[PDB]
Length: 572
Ligand SMILES: *[C@@H]1O[C@H](CO)[C@@H](O[C@@H]2O[C@H](CO)[C@@H](O)[C@H](O)[C@H]2NC(C)=O)[C@H](O)[C@H]1NC(C)=O
Ligand SMILES: COc1ccc2cc3[n+](cc2c1OC)CCc1cc2c(cc1-3)OCO2
Ligand SMILES: *[C@@H]1O[C@H](CO)[C@@H](O)[C@H](O)[C@H]1NC(C)=O
Image 1 (cartoon, helix red, strand yellow):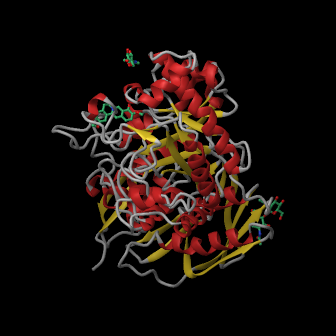
Image 2 (cartoon, rainbow, N blue to C red; image 1 turned 180 degrees about the vertical axis):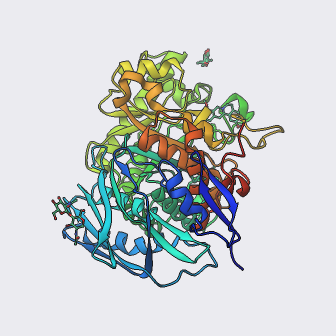
Image 3 (cartoon, rainbow, N blue to C red; image 1 turned 60 degrees about the horizontal axis):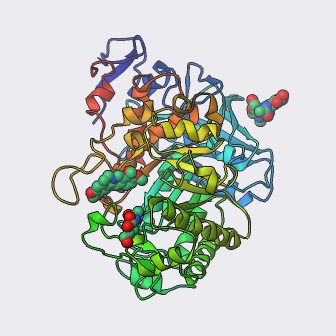
């Protein structure tokens, strides 16, 4: 069957009109109308520099797309892999069940990597790129991507793939004829936190996530790989941790699997950042070691935030031999990360107090048993754990901790320093802690629970009702949450943001809907920091959702497809 409608741009809105045969004007398909009716067309995220999309499209032979790398170097296999994936991303323009006519011009993609040896992740890496498309001769297209590193190069490959549209009226694959794009991100840390300990996530689902992250230029997969409920990380030096801590023998993450994920991410510009939360958020796996306290302590509401309770015992010297082995095994397989997340989630003082060995350790020292003295013990633990982390990675590298009582800006300088520790922020953007931390020079990663906790809104998992941070955070609230508004003058200290998917109520089955397309809103906010609000990005957000679905992502549905086909009629 054949498409019946056509679309025509009118005041920045594609209006659906009947495709009457008695017309001399060529019918426009829906996406062809959108590509030029919209200020930024079908691009997500919108570029930050020049965004010249011209006015016309060119028909393209899908089979005549060839990529040529002009500068060889150490990133040859990376550029070759990113070039091979480029054609699959072009086929994403075509709806499933439709076949384009193998007709039209040929495309020449010219990749220019100005530093073809650089392939390390760093907060200072250059993700910029230049993209220009123009006719070449009489039957060819010259698409030239120029970037200072491979990572910017494959960002430009991503943007180039979004410049293809499928004409489902005529079954023609089209491309923007004359493009001039210069682009670079506003923030260097654009991440997603995946909790794979409160519930297991298949390795295939994790790599599907990375695929969708690269599609919107997110670059950091924060792998919250352990917690109280399970220990799926296969640590070779301490094998009892995962053998006793895993939910099942197959719900683990082997060295080979992690190397797969890490390499999969590197090929797509995604740094895989591992976290070992400590000294709280520990439990299963540590049985028979006597290195924890209050594991499964009852009543749990007296001893921890959520069951099961359990914290490391920092007074045992053997603890830091365990941690050193854990970090070392992590550093072996997570060999592309430049940052290590050490958790620092809120420690329960009632739990540490209920241990005699801990109380004796503090009486033996010059400490009492008050709130201030358990801050002594926490900093005592963090100081030694930090030493082992440095040794394990064979290098002093940035460490991340959460906002907590340990990182309260009023006394954080007693324990940490702004050069060694990055602070991940879960508090709201109007919380005084953010201003105080910024004035002390600390660098921040924004994960405000009122706009970036992707677990909020569902039913309660203890008792009845809804979970603690309900209501559900729509993509509009994710888009409008701006770190520049939150940090103001200190915005350069903000390294970026990170959508947090805690997995008390999420696993392999719910992964796609939890993250997409809401994380794409965070992707544009962190890449472009637009002065405009979500309503200006609404039409493009609807398209990027459809693109996710085409990739095989079970993305959440935002609006009726009728609204997508009838821009302007769905408003409030
Ligand atoms: C493809 O297009 C690119 C950019 O439009 C061309 O590269 C430019 O070449 C001119 C001279 O011919 C230089 O002054 C510019 O600095 C180049 N731009 C960049 C970004 O490198 C390229 O020559 C074209 N290739 C073909 C085969 O037509
Ligand atoms: C780190 O930020 C976090 C992280 C996790 C948090 C978890 C919970 N709370 C704040 C949190 C928080 O804000 C402090 C509020 C109380 C609460 C009750 C619960 C629950 C979870 C939580 O599940 C069972 O009943
Ligand atoms: C620790 O336990 C003792 C009881 O021996 C109590 O007096 C003290 O207040 C407790 N500390 C905290 C922080 O609750």
